[PDB]
Length: 109
Length: 189
Length: 93
Ligand SMILES: *[C@@H]1O[C@H](CO[C@@H]2O[C@@H](C)[C@@H](O)[C@@H](O)[C@@H]2O)[C@@H](O[C@@H]2O[C@H](CO)[C@@H](O)[C@H](O)[C@H]2NC(C)=O)[C@H](O)[C@H]1NC(C)=O
Image (cartoon, rainbow over all chains, first blue to last red; front, side, top):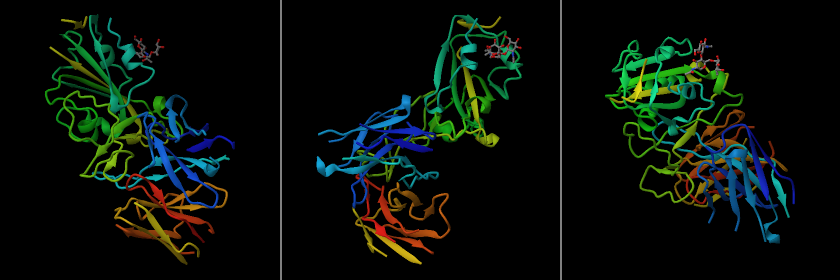
């Protein structure tokens, strides 16, 4: 299960192996010298993206590919990662969520 | 003749959370051709005798199809309980008809896993007979509102199956067709 | 719910504290220079397959610890308990 992202500069993330529409794909920003920020993500089966509290997040199951569109500052220079939302779940009560796979990263300036 | 070929030899099957239903009508139904077929591993009838199916005639006949794990096959029966019986596909305790299933490991399983098959883990309540809940809303399991992405007491109610050619039999996919018979529209020879 | 972790720079341990109780919904990551982060610990104390037994951790509610028994990388804590999801500052080994 690997994620393949587009090269440096829309930003794409193609899924190869593993679940797709059943698992949210999120985008995480990491500016140089900074930590990680979750900006939102989408479940292709739902078709609706949720955003962190500017950026358009979408996906299309038919190509097993997620997309993020950026448009119109210099302060946004960062490496952008895609990651799949996975969970370790037990009977009755499900108690965890994390990001398992992770693409190479796209450099946007 | 009834379009059984389009049910049993279908190119693809639906997930159990969103099982397909096809209404069969105005046709002649050959049942013994299936009963004595070596293609099936499970052929269990309730309310009817499998050997008299060719002589019996019915009104509406519904063919409900989906894919589940081999270990879950036992849940597709009246009076049974479990994650599939309660949250995906519930049969009435007075169900009339036959449940047909076969191993589809060599058909559906993929290297790396075929994750196109999903089932529900969570729901507010158990399903009514033949209720098909295909909503994709986040399930809340406490007083805390979700209002967004799943997390604590907020879950995406569906999970995919890791169906692989390297799985043990209980974890291999099975194609299940349930024939529900109401009681002259569909009639044998 | 924000996370605060310390020390910022370093057998060693790294601690991460939630400003609010988050049950067991935090995780830990290891990020090498120029690479994507990998999962170490999920559900507070459960190891990710492929992670050496040298790694362990525990905690509940607000106070959680990552322990390395004996991999110079930046380690992060993650909060998936509630929206918005966030991450810690990062600790350098
Ligand atoms: C489902 O298909 C099987 C297999 O039939 C073969 O594969 C099909 C996809 C198609 O290409 C057929 O022309 C092939 O023959 C059917 O099993 C056969 O049934 C006939 C009776 O009609 C019998 O004479 C054959 O010997 C059977 N072959 C085998 C391998 O069992 C089956 O009947 C089909 N099911 C339905 C409802 O049509």
